[PDB]
Image (tube, rainbow over all chains, first blue to last red; front, side, top):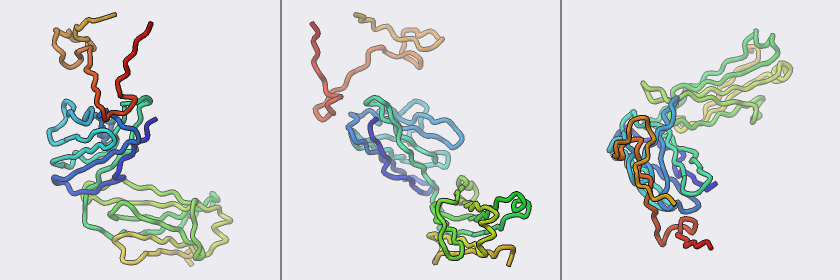
Length: 214
Length: 48
């Protein structure tokens, strides 16, 4: 399997006239690469074949370029519909391989996140599993750091992070982080806190609650 | 040995002798460059 990577993991740009995508391949492909646009919730659609010739049914704005190791996909004019995950697949040498893919984000004014912390419900405590949910609202860029601190001690590997897709109205991302603890473990620690670090935030914001609404 | 150049039919619709969608020329040009990788590079083969 030929090793291929996309140089921009994620690109954020406004819906204007500027777009660029780069794929680098360890072994020369001799101008044998293709690009696919996958809309979220939809099957992938071929954009270009061979990186030189536009596929049928593809708008003129879409363009492809590059040879051998370096392949570049540039969109002359960008529209909201165009934004989607983009995958480049190498077929020159068997086995055929697919790139990890690049999502084109929509550029928006940087916004500090809104942090909400919810203590576990009494019914959940009756169940015996305690979950603390940290909610982030309307934060751009999508990338964010959430750290759980219990008794001023960081917790790693006990949290699951869920991110919604970019909201259409304001181009913003919302993230929920869940910390799962056993009832005995939850009882042991009096204070639960979550530290969030974001570009918008001047300084990291920590939101905390005391056990049993202490 | 097959040397037929008849347009391949990949669709229910009659090919019509025109290489439209679902009709493709069977022979595909083979591209060779010096810069191309060794695997892509042309090898002359003779079998006795």
